Amino acid sequence: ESVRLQSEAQQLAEMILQSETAENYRNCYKRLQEDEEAGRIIRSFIKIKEQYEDVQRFGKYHPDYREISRKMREIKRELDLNDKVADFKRAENELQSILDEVSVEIGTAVSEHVK
Amino acid sequence: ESVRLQSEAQQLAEMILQSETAENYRNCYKRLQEDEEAGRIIRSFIKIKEQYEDVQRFGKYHPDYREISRKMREIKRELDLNDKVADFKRAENELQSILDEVSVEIGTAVSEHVK
Amino acid sequence: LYSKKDIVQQARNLAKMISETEEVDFFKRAEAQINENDKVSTIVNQIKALQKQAVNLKHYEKHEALKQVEAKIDALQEELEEIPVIQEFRDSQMEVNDLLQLVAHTISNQVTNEIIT
Amino acid sequence: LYSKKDIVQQARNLAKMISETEEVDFFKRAEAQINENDKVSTIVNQIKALQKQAVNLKHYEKHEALKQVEAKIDALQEELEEIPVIQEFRDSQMEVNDLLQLVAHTISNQVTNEIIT
């Protein structure tokens, strides 16, 4: 009576896991991890992010408030236009959609299942 | 040695308070408070806001998730286009700017005052 | 490999399998008792008319009048929220929502962990 | 009534009146001692050159090489942050910032409360 729900939710998930969207997500992440300059940009973004946040909580009186804010905007724009990053971020969403269409589908045949 | 700072910060504030930007902010708020349909829209916005937030924390499975979200967007758009609201929200910012130009000015002749 | 149609079907069955639960079953039962209740049916129609009267008071630019009716509507909804039959419904709805949430989560979380080999 | 020029002048004097404080005075004093310090001057030039070398390793697409220098820069900054003379500076800077914040706040708060008669 209880397992019958887990077992089917596990099937549905293992299905999504061996779906076209998943096999893609995988390969895009592999392409990104193996890419080195995307790595260069990512490591940088990591550093600038921290700096930004520190300055941000220090307030607008900070000497590099304007600068670190540009540095932040700019590094984002390097990720935004990096193919391997872009490719993965798209692949991530395609999967996120699969997840939500499923979430919606579960909710639909419960709302209508009352009538 | 101590009061000399408060007294001047109070002068600066009492100046801003009897500035053109202030006398305007005042009259715009009076115009808005005395306006009744802007009031109708405002009272409504107050109700929809609460409803929105409740549904928002209930999650996307809620029956009126889509509806209350539209109702939210739409009432905002009624404030956005209400003249008396718009007029006041502009007057609010003009003052907020006065405040920040001052904040910046205090910070400038401290940074350069080192040299 | 599976297409989105396979996965949407697999989900539509789990959705029925979720309608086949204590929780959902309780929900319909409280849902039955609130429109059956003629105190709830009273207010939902008292306010239904009061709402339609407000449309007229919108056209007829009357501050005091439209807010007299408005203050009477909002208070009548809060008063309707104090009925124990709807109080039961509001809870059962939340309980159903939690199972749907839990189901949805257990799914995304398996996927998000297992995805990278 | 006053124009924005009157108010910007009134502020520019308070700014000097703020430079005429214990806090700001302490700040310049710690500021003096860090570039006077030839351990700080060592690292700020060691890293200054290391930074310029990284520009070359950007052109010359070399993953391992650019991150060898990168890992050496970031660690050398953290090591520079452990110098007590700069540690003093970082604090005095914060103390100055707080007075500037407090001043700015006391001003907006008087205005935002008094504005509506």
Image (cartoon, coloured by chain):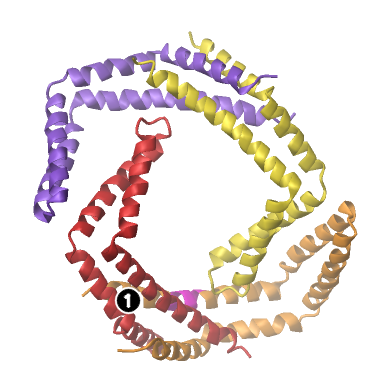
Chain colours: A yellow, B red, C purple, D orange
Q: Quadrant of the C terminus of chain B?
A: bottom right
Q: Looking at the image, which residue is at 19% across and 63% down?
A: B35
- Please tell me how many numbered marks the rendered image carries: 1
Depth check, front residue: A96 or A63: A96
- Position of residue C56 relative to residue B32, above or below, is above
Left/right of residue D34 with respect to residue D38 in the rendered view:
left
Q: Nearer the viewer, residue B2 or B5?
A: B5
The magenta segment: D98-104
The picture places residue B66, in percent across and down from the top left corner, at 39, 36
Compared across the picture, whether C49 is left or right of D30 comes to left
Q: Is residue A45 magenta?
A: no
The quarter of the displayed image where residue C54 is located: top left
Percent position of residue A109, x then y:
44, 18
Above or below D115: residue A82? above
Per the picture, the main secondary structure of the magenta-coloured stretch is helix
* Left or right relative to D80: residue D69: right
Give the residue drawn at x 56%, y 14%: A8
Residue D99: in magenta span = yes
Instruction: Please tell me how crowded label 1 is: few (under 14), some (14-19), or many (20+) other residues with Cα within 10 Å.
Output: some
- Which residue matches tag 1? D110
The image quadrant of residue C42 is top left
- The one nearer the camera, C89 or A17, is A17
Q: Residue at x 12, y 25 (%)?
A: C39
Query: Quarter of the image containing the N terminus of chain B?
Result: bottom left
Amino acid type at mark 1? Gln
Of helix, strand and loop, which one carries label 1? Answer: helix
